[PDB]
Image (cartoon, rainbow, N blue to C red):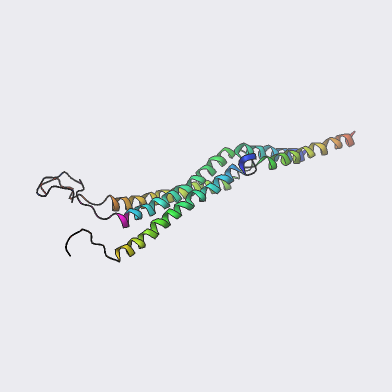
């Protein structure tokens, strides 16, 4: 969960760079991709949770 | 010699001509750096301007934004520097010549 | 490079930065070169006017 909190805000800021142009989308997609894996990660836990 | 000998002239109306050739480029030399001055500084300007938008956002790292904002601060100072360089040159280029701030019979 | 957003507009900014100022340095140069050359033009004294010497 905190991972997402961390990894999302990153991805969150990353777009802000692409919003500032400070990143390209490659940073973005991967960053987004980088994020999504987090989501992929977490759900399993809850899955595992149950 | 631009004037009419023995005529009366206004102030600073330049009736002679030095050869600007040396200085004229000399003025340019500063005019070059000023551009270089504004250039490097302008980019700094954009840099802070971008970062400023980061302000309150994540990566900004108040130190770092400050780093550029300095660079903003720092670069523009150089901007002021070159501008004078242009200025000193210009006043050394259009300096020539007319004339004894006084406006009178030549 | 910016054709598909592969860099940082910041970055490209920086690139143009020097590319901007670089030529200005060039300008600082050609201005320089002419300077001495002008002096070399001073050498080889030109009659500033025409007439019987």
- The front one of C26 and A34 is C26
- The front one of C53 and C41 is C53
In the rendered view, does C48 fall on the left or right side of C14?
left
Which residue is drawn at the image coordinates 47% and 47% (left, top)?
B39
Residue C33 vertical placement versus A46 (above, below): below
Residue A47 vertical placement versus C6 (above, below): above
Percent across and percent down for residue C20 are 49, 48
Percent across and percent down for residue B92 are 29, 53
Which residue is drawn at the image coordinates 17% and 60% (left, top)?
C51
Q: Where, by quadrant of the figure, is residue C50 drawn?
A: bottom left
Is residue C46 shown in magenta? no
Q: Can residue B31 be seen in this view?
A: yes
Q: Is residue B77 visible?
A: no
Q: Where, by quadrant of the figure, is residue C48 drawn?
A: bottom left
> How many numbered marks does the figure carry?
0
In the rendered view, does B30 fall on the left or right side of B59?
left
Q: What stretch is highlighted in magenta?
A: B12-23
Q: Residue furthest front?
A: C52
- The front one of B49 and B92 is B92
Which residue is drawn at the image coordinates 38% and 49% (left, top)?
B83
Percent across and percent down for residue A3 are 76, 41
Q: Where, by quadrant of the figure, is residue A39 drawn?
A: top right
Residue A45 vertical placement versus B22 (above, below): above
Main secondary structure along the magenta-highlighted residues: loop
- The front one of B35 and A14 is B35
In the rendered view, does C4 fall on the left or right side of B11?
right
């Amino acid at each position: 969960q905190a991972q997402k909190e961390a990894i999302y805000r990153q991805l969150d800021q990353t777009t802000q760079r692409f919003n500032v142009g400070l990143v390209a989308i490659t940073d973005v997609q991967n960053a987004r991709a980088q994020y999504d894996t987090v989501l992929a990660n977490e759900v399993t836990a809850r899955n595992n949770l149950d | 010699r631009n004037f009419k000998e023995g005529s009366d002239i206004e102030a600073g109306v330049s009736l002679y001509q030095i050869d600007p050739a040396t200085y004229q480029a000399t003025y340019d030399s500063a005019k070059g750096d000023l551009a270089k001055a504004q250039a490097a500084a302008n980019i700094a300007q954009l840099t802070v301007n971008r970062y400023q938008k980061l302000l309150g956002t994540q990566y900004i790292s108040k130190q770092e934004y400050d780093q550029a904002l300095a660079d903003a601060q720092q670069a523009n100072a150089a901007v002021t520097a070159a501008k004078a360089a242009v200025e000193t040159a210009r006043i050394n280029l259009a300096y020539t010549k007319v004339t004894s701030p006084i406006s009178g019979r030549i």
